Image (cartoon, coloured by chain):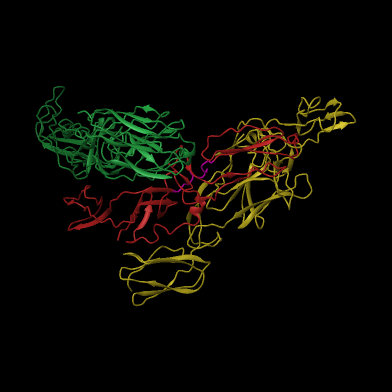
Chain colours: A yellow, B red, C green
Amino acid sequence: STANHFNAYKLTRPYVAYCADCGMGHSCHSPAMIENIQADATDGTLKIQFASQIGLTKTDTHDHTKIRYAEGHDIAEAARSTLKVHSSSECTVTGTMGHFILAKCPPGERISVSFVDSKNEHRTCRIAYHHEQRLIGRERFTVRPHHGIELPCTTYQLTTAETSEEIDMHMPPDIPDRTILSQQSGNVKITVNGRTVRYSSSCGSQAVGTTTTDKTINSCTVDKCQAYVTSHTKWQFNSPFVPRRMQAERKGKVHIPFPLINTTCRVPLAPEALVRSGKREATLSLHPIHPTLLSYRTFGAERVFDEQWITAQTEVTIPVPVEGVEYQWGNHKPQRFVVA
Amino acid sequence: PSPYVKCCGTAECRTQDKPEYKCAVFTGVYPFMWGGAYCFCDSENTQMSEAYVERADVCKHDHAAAYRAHTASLRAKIKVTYGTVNQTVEAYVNGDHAVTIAGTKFIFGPVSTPWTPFDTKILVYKGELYNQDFPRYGAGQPGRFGDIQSRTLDSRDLYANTGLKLARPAAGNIHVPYTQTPSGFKTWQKDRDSPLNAKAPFGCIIQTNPVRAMNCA
Amino acid sequence: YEHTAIIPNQVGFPYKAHVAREGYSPLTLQMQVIETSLEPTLNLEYITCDYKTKVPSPYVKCCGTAECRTQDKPEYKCAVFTGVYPFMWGGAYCFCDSENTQMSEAYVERADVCKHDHAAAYRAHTASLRAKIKVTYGTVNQTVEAYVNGDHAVTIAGTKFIFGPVSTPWTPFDTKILVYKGELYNQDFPRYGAGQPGRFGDIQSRTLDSRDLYANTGLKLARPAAGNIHVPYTQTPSGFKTWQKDRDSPLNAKAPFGCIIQTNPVRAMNCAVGNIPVSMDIADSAFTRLTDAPVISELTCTVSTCTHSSDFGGIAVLSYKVEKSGRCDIHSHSNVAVLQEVSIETEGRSVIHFSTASASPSFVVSVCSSRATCTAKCEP
C-alpha cells in the first residue's frame, strides 16, 4: 500500500502516545503527542511526527477526510480537515502521511497541533521548538512574490509519499492503566475492550487471556488481580515518550513521506546603489531595503574587507584603492570597481 | 526507544552497538497510562533506557565536508592572436600539458606563485568555504565544529564525542530524559564564519565543484 | 597523565617507556610498529597504450582522380597516389588503362588492450605514514593503526594517542612516478600529450578513460604496389612496447629507507626510516595505585650472561627480596639496554632478557620504583 499509502500505514495500528503537556499541565497517551518535528530544508517546511496515523480510516482507507487517531479503543477516527497547526499563527499545512504531518508556519518558539475527533473541542498539544526564519540570500525578506531572484534552496520535497527513509515500528504495547478488571463483591472480572488486558494477577483470573472478553476469578480483591496490555496488527511509532510496553522489538518499515528535494527560491534584490567617486574613496549611498547584509572587499593584496547588515539609508565609505575594491552590497551581482 | 520497563521487576542492562549507544536502568517506575496494566507492581520496577548516537539522515542529502589540502595548479584559457591565427586555447598552467597551437607550441609556466586562497585544512559547507582548525579526526571536543566527525562521507564508522547524558525520569510518564549536548553541526552552521569568497586576497572567486579559486589576481 | 616520547620507526624494535605518575606504580608502555607506508598523492597525465593505425579500404578511382576527406582520428592521414594499376587477382579493380588514383587513409587509435592494462604516470604530492603500533600499556594490550599526521587521533581504551605529525618525507616519491604493470619507476613524463615520437608515451593520455587521445606518432603513407591495393604506411616504432619492454630498474627495487614499494595505492610499506613520535594521554585506570603495589626491596642486580652483539643478548639475574608480592614493572631507566618485558614476578632471583647491543653494558633497571645499575661486559 503505497499509492494508497494507507496499506503500509495501516499494517501498523496507528495508536496514541504519551504527551506530558497539552494545555497547562495535562498530557496523557493522547493523539496530541508530537513525537519529532524535523525540518531539513532551506525552503522552510516543518515535518512533525504526529501521534495518530492521520489519513487512514477505520479500515485504513486512503481517506482525504480521514485522521486516524487513538482512543482507549484503537479507532479514534477524526476529520482530516479539522486538524490545525499553529506556530504563532495558523501555519499552512501541506500534507499528512500517517504519523508524519508536513506544513509551513511563520517564525515562532513552539508548534501547537489541535484536532477534535469525537472529543469536545480540539484536543491539542503544543511542543516547544524554536522555529527560526533562517533564509539564504543577500537580503532577509520573507516575500516570495518578488520578481527579483532565483537561488538554490533545499526543502522537504512535496512528492507523493512512498518512502525515502522509513521509520521503524515494533512493540505492540502494553499500557499502564488497569481499570478494566473490577471486583463484583468477591470476584475479579476482566471484560473485553480496546485495551488488551492480559490476565496478570497473583492467581486466578489474572493468569491468562488478553482482554477481548470477560474472565472471572472469585476470591478476588483490589490487590491480587492484575491487568496487562497486549496488541495486534501494529507496532509502536518509536515509543518516544511511549513506555516500551512490549517484551521485544521487531521493526516494520513506514516510508517517511515528504522526502526532501532540492528546489529553487525567489529572493528579491533591493535598489542597487549610488557611487560617489573621490580621491581613492567612494560613497555607496544606499537607501535601505528590507534589510540585508552588504559586503565590500578590497580586491588585490591583503584585502581590507568588511560586511554590514544595512538596514537604513546611509553611505558606505568603500575604500576604492589602486587595485580596486569588490563591493557586493545586497542581492545583486558581486561587481566591484576600479579607481575612478 | 520505548524503555524496557519492568512494572514491577528490575531488569538487566544490555549494551547496544551505536557510537552514542549508552544505556541505564533507573529504579522506581510507576506508570499511569490508559491502555492495559503496566504499572501493576507497587515498587521494584526498573526503566532501562538506551540511546544510540546515529548520523543525521540529511547527511546523504547534505553534509559539511572539511578537507586538508596540498598545492594546486593554475589553469587558463589564453586567447592567442598570432597574426592570421586568432583562437583561444585552454591548458593547465603547471607546465606539463603543453598546448599545440596551429603551428604554435604553447607552454604555460609553471608559475611558482602559491599565493592561493587554499588554507591548511579548509571546510566546504554548502559551497561555502572557510579555512579553519579542523578538529582531531574523530578526536573532536563536543560542542564545536565537528561534534560528530566523518571518517568517510558515507563512511561506515561514526566518530563523535557528543555529550549525551541520560537521566532518571519523573513518575507516571515514561520520560526517558537524556541530556544531549548542543548541536555542534547546527552550532557550526549557525555561527558560520566569513565565506571563502569573503576576503579572498587576489580577488579570485572560490568556486567548488572542485574547490578552485577562479580569476586569480 | 600524558607522556610524550618517540619509538624509532623500524618495525619490530620494542620501544619501552617508563611512565611516571605520583602514587601509581611505574607505568610500562611497550610500543611496536608494523607497516607504516607513506602513500604519496598522485595525479595522472598519461596512459601509454599501444597506438594502432587503421588503414581503411582503398578508394580506387579506377579510372579517375580521387578525393580526400578530412579524418577525425589522431593519426588520421589521407593520400591520393595518382595513377594506380588495377590488376587484382580476384578481378581487375581498375577497368581503365591509366588516370586512376588511390585514396588511402588511416587513423591512429588507442589499442583495446589499454582497458585491459595501461601504463599510468602521475605527478606526486606528499603522503602519510600509516602504522600499526602494538601498544602493551599495562593490562591494556592492543594494536592501533593510524596515519602519522596526528589529526586522526587514536582513541585507545582510555588511551589518547597522537602519533605524529611526521618528521621527514624521505620517501621514494619523485616529481613523476610511472606505475606500469604494477611496477613503480621514476621517469620523466613528456609534455602533456604533445610528446616526441619514439618515446615512452608516444600516445599521450589526458585521461586514462579520456575521450581525446594525444599523440605524436609518426605516421606516413606509402605509394603501394600496383595490380592490387597495397596500402604502405610508415608509422613510428612501437614505443609503448619500446617503453614497456626495455624498461629500467623498477623503483620497488633499489628503494632507499628499506621500504617495500607496494602500490595498489602507491605506498612504501615498512619504510624503515626515522623515529615516529607519539604523545599518549594515559588512562587514569592505567596508574595502578602505588599503595596497592608489590612492596619491593633488596634490589640486587647480577649481570649473568652478556652477548654484546646479539638480538636477545642480556641474561640478567636481578634479585629483589620485596615485602609484598605482586607483578613488578621492570621498565629500566637505562637507554643503553633493553628489557624483555615489564612483568616481574614475586621478588627473588628473577632472570630477565636484558638485551643491550653496547659492548660495555651498564644499565639502570627500574623494578617497581626500585632502580639499580647492572654493569658487565658482553660477548662479541
Does the magenta-highlighted stretch encompass residue C237?
Answer: no
Position of residue C35 measured from the top left corner of the image (x, y, whole percent):
32, 34
Question: Is B184 rendered above or below residue C309?
Answer: below
Residue A203 visible in the shown view = yes
* Quadrant of the frame with the N terminus of chain B: top right
Position of residue C212 measured from the top left corner of the image (x, y, whole percent):
26, 41
- Front one among A130 and C312: C312
Asked where in the image residue A333 lies, by quadrant, the reply is bottom left
Q: Residue furthest top?
A: C90
Position of residue C134 measured from the top left corner of the image (x, y, whole percent):
37, 33
Question: Is B11 rendered above or below residue A130?
Answer: above
Question: Is C9 rendered above or below residue A272?
Answer: above
Magenta-colored segment: predominant secondary structure: loop
Residue A162 visible in the shown view = no
Does the magenta-highlighted stretch encompass residue B58?
Answer: yes
- Front one among B165 and C161: C161
* Quadrant of the frame with the C terminus of chain B: bottom left
Position of residue A303 measured from the top left corner of the image (x, y, whole percent):
35, 65
Question: Is C277 rendered above or below residue C100?
Answer: below
Q: Is residue A19 left or right of residue C372?
A: right
Q: Residue furthest right?
A: A185
Stretch in magenta: B53-64
